Length: 229
Ligand SMILES: O=C(O)c1c(F)ccc2c1O[B-](O)(O)[C@@H]1C[C@H]21
Ligand SMILES: [Zn+2]
Ligand SMILES: [Zn+2]
Image 1 (cartoon, helix red, strand yellow):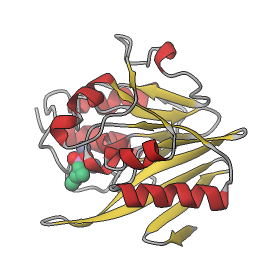
Image 2: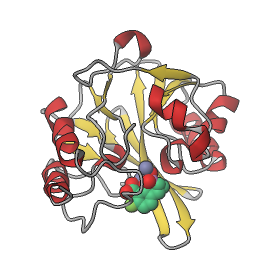
Image 3: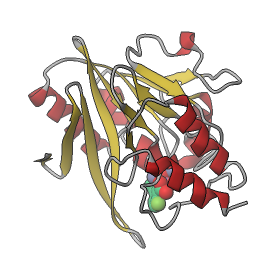
């Protein structure tokens, strides 16, 4: 099920959806896997999250060229940390239109990231303002509230059973909520639950640092976050 491609791993999750995985050896954490998504929509490819680095992100684009061979119409990144946004320059070098939460773009320089070219804004109920996410096809972008970070966003894939929680969601057996350095501890549980409520049909939950899981990832993440209050 896993395809090794250079130093990256790709896993098909649905007829039109693949998970990309890249690794960074970070001092104190080991070699951390980070996951994003690749979605074919008709004659276009859409990407969710970069790899950790520009070089790894260029390798994602190389895999897409070899395995799908359709243009990458856009990428959306899910917050301003390196696992999600470290490869922005590779997307720009490739001519790909890039999107992030407006707040992610504002935070990018101080986080050591390069901003995306376009900013998403969100209605009070969390759904993206559609004018700011043109041509997103089946990608349904939802801001669940502050959690792992204040700017974290999530993405469902219409027509599939898949939703992507990024670094907000940890797997159903996780022992901790990971890196809480920029987290909103009081609102985390509610934000995890809001993600689940936004995508009630999603039976496959994809996340940054573990393999795809059932919705027990959502309930378990929220239950762990209940203890932060
Ligand atoms: O998502 C996490 O919880 C996480 C972690 F547990 C360890 C290290 C990192 C994490 O994500 B990050 O904050 O986005 C960043 C790349 C670093
Ligand atoms: Zn993060
Ligand atoms: Zn992370």
